[PDB]
Amino acid sequence: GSASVKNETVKLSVGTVSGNPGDTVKVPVTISQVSTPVGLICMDISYDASKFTVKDVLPNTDLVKDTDNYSFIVNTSTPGKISITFTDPTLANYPISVDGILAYLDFIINSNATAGDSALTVDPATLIVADENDKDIKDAASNGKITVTGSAPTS
Image (cartoon, rainbow, N blue to C red; front, top):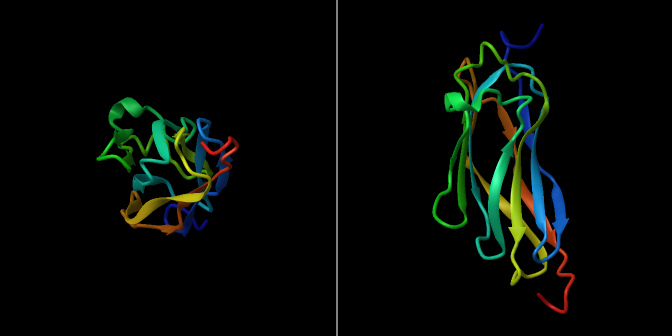
């Protein structure tokens, strides 16, 4: 009924994870309350480049399919910024209108990283979630918070 022909408010959610210095932490970006197929996703992750270091990111292939159609775009910007963009032209074949995790962000917590809570600032302006009707339909709050335990003498 109210989906596709009607656009809803898609929540982009992230949570709080914990890790140790030298431990690799994976931050899942959760997409919730989606019913209309999304096609345009862009997000800038501005994080602490000294405390964390991104390895790579895992796209959820349930949602993002046939990434070879340039549906998967990751530009590793100047240290601390990750420009991630998922734009899929294959949205009629694969309608991302189902919930789950969008992508998993893998960050290594640095050896010299200080304990405490440090959140990853996902830039809300560069964060764009538009469907095939090109409407930004996101209720988004995304600051992936990583609680560094600091389980060591110090680091």
